Length: 277
Length: 277
Ligand SMILES: Nc1ncnc2c1ncn2[C@@H]1O[C@H](COP(=O)(O)OP(=O)(O)O)[C@@H](O)[C@H]1O
Ligand SMILES: Nc1ncnc2c1ncn2[C@@H]1O[C@H](COP(=O)(O)OP(=O)(O)O)[C@@H](O)[C@H]1O
Ligand SMILES: [Mg+2]
Ligand SMILES: [Mg+2]
Image 1 (tube, chains in turn red, yellow):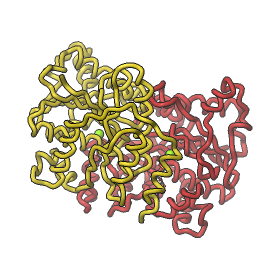
Image 2: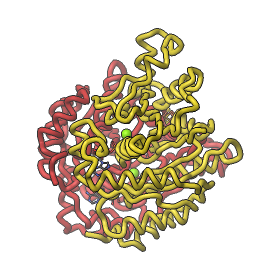
Image 3: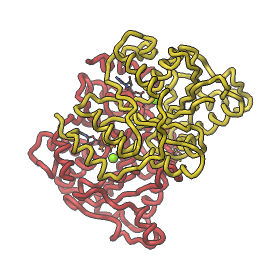
């Protein structure tokens, strides 16, 4: 068995940083993990690979001729802790559907046998600002059974969490895609943890971890590393280890209860977020 | 003549706040303005209308039967300063293309004669995290001749600005869509203004205004108002008046020069952004 997990969230919220650090912690534990980048930014594996980014399946297929001329051994790349990494890519802006490369990538990986019995986890790092096309495919096509949403006390981040939850509800009749939890990537604001806990409770899930804002992340990323690799003794490394432990142990996978915009606004007002100075 | 402008940018960067405040300042000056919401969040007109949000063309068409059963006089709503407001809407998450409602809305507005000679400006408030489907339509179909990108020293915000610029370049052979400038919506970080000026120069454009981070925005928005209406004497009101003046006077509309990710990273490192504590 392997657990298929997808990390969703609005752009810039911390999906790739959180995913790569969580996965590094899992590898440090002895888990075998694959990361599948499903964001056109295509930098979802750079901290595992110590790289600028990674050439995408869409790019490699175009240079090879067709995706079928690609071999899995040429596409997947291993980095820190033996974590295997692949990037979907996507069309250039203004051309075709930004999510089209995700469909091509996931189907290629399945056909080519990337989902070897030995994997313990697959993480898809998925753009979440729209829930359509290839970005909806992990949910619509039952590819990621456990969705974790990175979010913060930002209204936009919570709105995205609600929209992703609506997509999960839409496809609940088929497959087994469920919301596994919210991950609060802190903006260093008062009561933020309480706010995301409250949002999670309203959606029917939980806040699986509160990730502090910590500049060690920037220092590690400037060096193309997870915090786990860059400074295993960092306080922030232990934060990602705690998140990884809780993901491993998590058994709550729900069909979420999307909320109204009135409920979101009440949450913000209640927890004095919009009133913090 | 009327100037057709589109405000693009990543989610949560400040498009709707900036657009509505800029437009309120234009109306305060005596300009006639229409705002067309092109973001599924569909709250791009609430501060002009003093409202929760606005019912969308997609919603109204579904209740009426077809979009052709709708009348312009039932769709457009006027708020502060006589500013006319409409929201496109979009499909629910997981269903169909998130941008489909933008195509329906803009075509409806054109067919129904919303672009009356008396308008001085139309502003489209467009989701910019992907540049495809209906979100690319204002560029692809030559609807917004002047694109202004709201951005900040956030790497994701600058990446979005570059991707939108790539979309402008893609469609430069036809129509007349051009990049008019970057608007820095400040994160209260050192040298941010210099950073966005540098990015603008690399793209071939300009930073048309640096909008400070100011909590009066939250206080006005809690009351469903632009700062312009809420407190015309606020320092931030004068900031939006300065932005509006510079938009009115702006004559630089370029085919931009998208940059590499290496150039973006160098910009961040140069201006010690990622190294600010
Ligand atoms: N917990 C954190 N502390 C400090 N910086 C963070 C943290 N999480 C993310 N970041 C920073 O935020 C930026 C965006 O994170 P990223 O993971 O790339 O977002 P996404 O993948 O959701 O677009 C990066 O510069 C990263 O260094
Ligand atoms: N200059 C500013 N100062 C303070 N808060 C701001 C400013 N600009 C935007 N905001 C806040 O940021 C949030 C997102 O702005 P919004 O315009 O809704 O973003 P977008 O439309 O790009 O998703 C809102 O809560 C708004 O109050
Ligand atoms: Mg990312
Ligand atoms: Mg908006």
